[PDB]
Amino acid sequence: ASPFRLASAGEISEVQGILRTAGLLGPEKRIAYLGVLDPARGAGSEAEDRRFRVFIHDVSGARPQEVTVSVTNGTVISAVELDTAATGELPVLEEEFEVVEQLLATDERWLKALAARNLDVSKVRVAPLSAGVFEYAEERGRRILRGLAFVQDFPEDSAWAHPVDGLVAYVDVVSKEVTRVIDTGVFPVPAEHGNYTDPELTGPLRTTQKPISITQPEGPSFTVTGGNHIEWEKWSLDVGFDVREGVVLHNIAFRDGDRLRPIINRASIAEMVVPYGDPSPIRSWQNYFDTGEYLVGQYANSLELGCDCLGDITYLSPVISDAFGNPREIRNGICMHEEDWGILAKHSDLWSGINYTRRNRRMVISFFTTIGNYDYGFYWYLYLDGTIEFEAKATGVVFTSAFPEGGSDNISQLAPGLGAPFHQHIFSARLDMAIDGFTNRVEEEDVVRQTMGPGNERGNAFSRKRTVLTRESEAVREADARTGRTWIISNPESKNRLNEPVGYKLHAHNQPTLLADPGSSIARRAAFATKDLWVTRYADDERYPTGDFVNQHSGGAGLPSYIAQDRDIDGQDIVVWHTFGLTHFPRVEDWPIMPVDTVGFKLRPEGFFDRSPVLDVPAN
Amino acid sequence: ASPFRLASAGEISEVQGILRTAGLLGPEKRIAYLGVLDPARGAGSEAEDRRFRVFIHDVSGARPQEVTVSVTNGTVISAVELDTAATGELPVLEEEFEVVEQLLATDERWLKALAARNLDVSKVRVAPLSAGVFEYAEERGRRILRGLAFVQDFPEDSAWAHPVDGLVAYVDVVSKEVTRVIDTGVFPVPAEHGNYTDPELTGPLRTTQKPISITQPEGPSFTVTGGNHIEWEKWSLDVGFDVREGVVLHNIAFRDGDRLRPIINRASIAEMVVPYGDPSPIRSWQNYFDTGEYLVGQYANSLELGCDCLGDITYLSPVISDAFGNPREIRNGICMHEEDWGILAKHSDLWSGINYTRRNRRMVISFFTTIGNYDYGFYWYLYLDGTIEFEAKATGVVFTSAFPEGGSDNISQLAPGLGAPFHQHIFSARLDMAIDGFTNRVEEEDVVRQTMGPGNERGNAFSRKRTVLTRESEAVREADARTGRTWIISNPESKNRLNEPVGYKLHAHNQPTLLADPGSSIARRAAFATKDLWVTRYADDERYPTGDFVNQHSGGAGLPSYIAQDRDIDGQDIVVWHTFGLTHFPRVEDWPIMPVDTVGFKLRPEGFFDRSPVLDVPAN
Ligand SMILES: [Cu+2]
Ligand SMILES: [Cu+2]
Ligand code: NA
Ligand code: NA
């Protein structure tokens, strides 16, 4: 009965039927995106209306459409034709990936390039990559993918070990034309293999690891009701899944006594961008918007018990649409479990004689996705003490190139002749805040150093300052690790027992933001990534920091256009957008398969509670 | 047979006997510090010589002595009388703690202050705190403790909830004289209790937590030999314990094929300072050097199975000396165990069809200490992939004060009338490096942004720069989170298969350093804490960043005096000193007992290995 329940196979089949009868899903149509819409603000009228948003592509060249459908009422609510030269192309379709390699295999220019390198075309894999917006006027309004080539010596070979540098092609995947083939010169194809399951490379496997058994004899401490509503250790929330964003957390609240207190209305990773820092023309266009261009949810892995998720695991299997509107289940796509997390609080008091120790635990909600050579884990954590944390885990195989004779300022050497271009992995977390309700404000908190003198005669004092962000035009903020800068989201109308506004403090990792020149195409398309924190006034249609249609979109849709409205954010319904990322200079240890590296952020209560919220945790 | 074995009870009893026969341990003597000396450099002569360093205090006022003893040969090697006005006082003795409260209970000025506040002297606990060096000329060369008062309403009451503000006393603990009693005015004593085991405060305990059982059916994967030598998943090390520093890690090495490769010769937390930022004269002198003044190892907790350390735990019980030279065992003072640590590496490859997942684990070595109201956990982690990490866990009860009418810029309100002064907790890690041997160097690595233009036509390139620190005078470095600054420790004479120097990269958390005015007493005494990174040339006697005798020492002994020698550090035997800390603005949630907060650092391999070192990990 909950409006936040996961989409069912029956709902998706009904959407397909509604579209087909409306004449909107003929044989030339493909669904590029399908997802449920969240309820509107103030939906307390109980009038449930399950609506779905659909992007419909046309493989014959006709204009795509954006369609909203009510499964409740069985009707098309709206259907708008899109001018993609203006508002952006639709996300990349899975079926367009294979088109690139197939089209190149019959192109005379491509074959000539492969012949010069003595490469069998049957052995050449082509990575189909998003195109961006650069200098090529003929690409305006067309669906372009760019392709980079890798050699697979045999069917089980890791092609990433054998990049074919000096060669790139551009493909129109609708007209099925190879627009350009660029060959800047022959590089030797690196010859060493990168097969991390080959005994020749691994050596004999270790026999020294003894098992660790994690069990829950009485089952887990959380409950799952209505398919996706979670209650755990005073936390209450709904776990959503969207094919673009992946796992989305709704209605995060904490049961404090007999009050259910809201904290975050919606939490998601609303964009992620991977920009490459190699100036070679073979790769200087390379930027992945994994969320906005590829849709990370549709490539979620099925997670294996004992291997991907260890312990007493409760799975969700979200349902998505395929390109034809058929429901497709991602079996075991979401892992949920609780984990011991060490000491929570401890004190041995000499005067009282009381020795006290309590243990911490966290609830984990996670999924994993694979996009080409990259694999990303998305982890949300809830802790006993009210802390909320997000962690991204990056692994997979690094994207490779030739390593040039004479070295490079922009590429690392991984093996003889084998390089890995510098790049970043940057995320945007969209946090639709609801600290004790919707009237919230953000303050920036800096440490304040004080000079020795009157009132500070020994020169030991220090303090802090808080600045309220009152309008969107002043709510674009940068990190300052040296001054311990954090941001507090508070409710000025809800006070704790000391008559202070209740709040939560955002702790960032203070990693570098986007490094590209501010005048670059990627800086314009990923403007969100140039600053650590943005605050907007909530609006229904301001969902993504990059806009609705990211693929081949020139710039002018997302956060910079939202904040130009300069809306009041002082005690209002607000959304915090936090940018955070990894800057990756690949090391030898990242090859041939990369150990996990992590980045994230956390929110901790700041006078939200009247005292420690974990005094009622038992002694274990 | 190992020279790095833990001190035995028999060794300590022999030291006691050697001292007594030498006439150095009469009834007026107390041992303030006793510890084993590490072997000298180049001890490959196998000529073992177990030597102990002892600080001997005299309760009659005679000069203390520093004594070195050989238990091997049964002789006093040297014994020097100390001029404490020059070189500093000895660490605080446990038996001097109780002296403060007892002496104040009979002082007419103290009693008058308590009478004005209607406090029963039998209910007043006095926190005995280190004195520092300030304006009081009569303190030069005397052992002073300062006392702050708290009311205990009944024997099991938490006195921290009832600070007696406006009152401080100074005590000479040798002459047994109260030198000064300062009363700046009556503050109400906060009345609410802070008893976190009282059902009135906790409410009914939760019944919702289901057990998590962590077991190892075949036992742990590590082995312990020679009492303290650890082998685990290619790591090899020796776990030492010193009464001042606590757990010390020796001879950290990694078995790469058939080579045992050194990484760190000695790792320890060599100082920690807790400076308070309240300018009130009642507390503006307050700075704890927990390591150097109090000796954190002697207050190590006995750690309880299932509560402090969960899983298949292997304990060490280090032996220390009491004040009279008797051996004292700290039962179950060190926990060692391995922990699952999630996904290590994962890739699902479309082209090869191979799906690959491996799990990570870490080895944990930890101890907990309690100093008054504060409890600190020290955790060392070794990971499969070669990462080394340290984490400090801070909990216990926050130090309190009155909350002034009209508020404070330097104190947080925790409960009606109850305050908590701002403060920091800053650590110094001393890392005697040995990356593939002792010829090491440090480079500072910054991200480099590049401007759009020729050779970077699309404005996407970025790079990095490395600066070698060649002499001590240029090796005092600051963090720069915005430029992604890290430090690489490399061996210029040991190269990987790509002919690059092998190395390890230090990743700091980039938290604020010491906030006090540079002209303050604490900035002079804790100069190490004003900068993030120092590199020195190794020397036997340069053990602590604050010098050997920190208590009441004016300044002029530690890192600033070492680096003035301006020694060559480019490809030499070097020591890295990393400062890192928490800046604590107490929150309501920290009361009445504080949930753990953490800070730390880590080192990751940087071309140390020829490829990923975890390819031989099995599928689980
Ligand atoms: Cu990367
Ligand atoms: Cu603190
Ligand atoms: Na909001
Ligand atoms: Na060294």
Image (spheres, coloured by chain):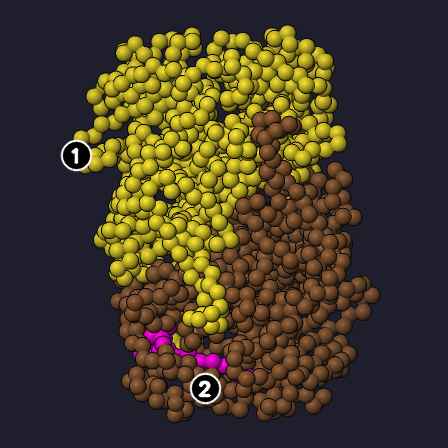
Chain colours: A brown, B yellow
Q: Is mark 1 within 8 Å of ligand 4?
A: no
Write the residue at 57% across / 45% down.
A484
User: In the drawing, does residue B545 fall left or right of residue B495?
Assistant: right
Q: CA distance from mark 1 to mark 2?
A: 71 Å
Residue identified by numbered label 2? A180
- Asked whether residue A435 is in view, the answer is no
- Asked whether residue B512 is in view, the answer is yes
Write the residue at 55% across / 80% down.
A93
Q: In what element is the residue under mark 2?
A: strand
User: In the drawing, does residue B381 fall left or right of residue A32?
Assistant: left
Name the front one of labels 1 and 2: 2
Residue identified by numbered label 1? B45
Chain of the residue where label 2 is placed in the rendered structure: A
Which range is magenta? Answer: A143-165
Write the residue at 60% across / 26% down.
A457
Q: Quadrant of residue A580?
A: bottom right
User: In the drawing, does residue A307 fall left or right of residue A568?
Assistant: left
Label 1 with label 2: CB-CB less than 8 Å:
no
Chain of the residue where label 1 is placed in the rendered structure: B
Q: Is mark 2 within 8 Å of ligand 1?
A: no
